[PDB]
Image (cartoon, rainbow, N blue to C red):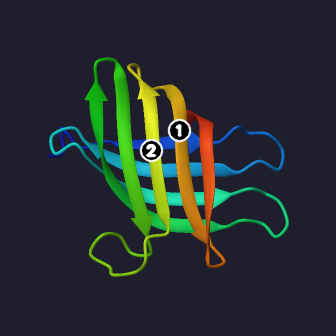
Amino acid sequence: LRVGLFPVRYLVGTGLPGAPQLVLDLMVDTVDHSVVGRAAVSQAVSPPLNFHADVWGSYVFRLAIVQISLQGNQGGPQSNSMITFYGELLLKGDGKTGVASYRYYSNGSWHEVENVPVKAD
């Protein structure tokens, strides 16, 4: 589905110094409505956050909001490794920007980031 296939990068975070930053190098099949890629999470604080997990999921356009629900781990969906990531992007009908929430797992603990801005590229 190369025609339906195409990549997209989502920067999820406020961008404030010391604030968490999510980068989403993902891919979108507009046929299967599937989503897959990598999730790098960093806050640039003490100690530096370096969360990386293969993330997969799907998107649902709704009348106009584009809702993407994503989940992630070490290896992707055929791996039995524990889920270390949940994210939901509620992009606007244009898809360029929008609000979003995500949870990454670190040090035996879940870290929740709610209502942070999203930009592509």
Which residue is painted at 45% across and 39% down in the image?
89
The location of residue 62, given as percent across then percent down, is 28, 25
* Element type where label 2 sits in the image: strand
Instruction: Decide which of 108, 79 is in the foreground and name it.
Output: 108
Asked if one can make out residue 40 in the rendered structure from this viewpoint, the answer is yes
Three-letter code, disc 1:
Ala
- Horizontal side of 101 relative to 7 (left or right) equals right
The location of residue 71, given as percent across then percent down, is 40, 59
- Horizontal side of 1 relative to 101 (left or right) equals left
The label on residue 100 is 1
Marks 2 and 1: CB-CB under 8 Å? yes
Quadrant the C terminus occupies = top right
Three-letter code, disc 2:
Glu
State which quadrant residue 37 falls in: bottom left
Which residue is painted at 44% across and 33% down in the image?
90
State which quadrant residue 36 falls in: bottom left
Which residue is painted at 40% across and 50% down in the image?
26
Residue at far bottom of view: 80
Decide: is 98 above or below 116: above
Instruction: Decide which of 78, 5 is in the foreground and name it.
Output: 78
The label on residue 88 is 2
Mark 2 or 1, nearer chain start: 2
The location of residue 47, given as percent across then percent down, is 82, 70
Residue neighbourhood size for the residue with mark 1, other residues' Cα within 10 Å, grouped as few (<14), some (14–19), many (≥20): many
